Image (spheres, coloured by chain):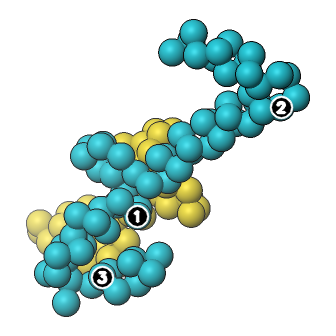
Chain colours: A cyan, B yellow
Amino acid sequence: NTLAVQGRTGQGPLATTFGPVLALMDNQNNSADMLNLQTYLTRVTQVRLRLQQIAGSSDPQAMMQMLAQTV
Amino acid sequence: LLRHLGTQNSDAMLYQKMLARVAHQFADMRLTDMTGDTDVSRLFFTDE
């Protein structure tokens, strides 16, 4: 958001080179569907849940290998 | 003789050019996709 303050106007299209970086904050992804930062932070939370599960009091020396075969 | 037909048919359609006059005083074309909330409405859920 600090990087989103100082590049909103061209000063739409951005006359500075903060163009493609501010295409990640919320670009309203009209058919250029590569990634949004809203979606990418959700995939971090799934890995947070899975890495919390193995440490979750189920002998994590075993549950890690119990996940390591799934890869 | 034809002007009265041109004003009686205008009784449904002189408002239609007045409708175009109000159309040009409004910039609200399409309500900019029927804007729901601070949800994205282009990431999913009739996105486009």
Are there few (<14), some (14-19), or many (20+) residues within 10 Å of tag 1?
A: some
Measuring from the top left, give residue B6's x and y in whole percent.
18, 67
Q: Assign a secondary structure to mark 3.
A: loop
Specify the amino acid type for callout 1: Met
Q: Which residue is drawn at 53% across and 50% down?
A: A41
Determine the CA span between mark 3 and mark 1. 11 Å
**Residue indicated by mark 3:** A7
Instruction: Say left or right for B3 vs A18.
Output: left
Judging depth in this view, the residue of B23 and A6 nearest the camera is A6
* Percent coordinates x, y for residue A16 in the rendering: 16, 81
Residue type, label 2: Gly
Q: Earlier in the sequence, mark 3 or mark 1?
A: 3
Q: Do the residues labelled 3 and 1 touch (CB within 8 Å)?
A: no
Q: Which amino acid does label 3 sit on?
A: Gly
Outermost bottom residue: A11
- Tag 2 residue: A56
- Crowding around mark 2 (Cα neighbors within 10 Å: few <14, some 14 to 19, many 20+) is few
* Residue A25 circle label: 1
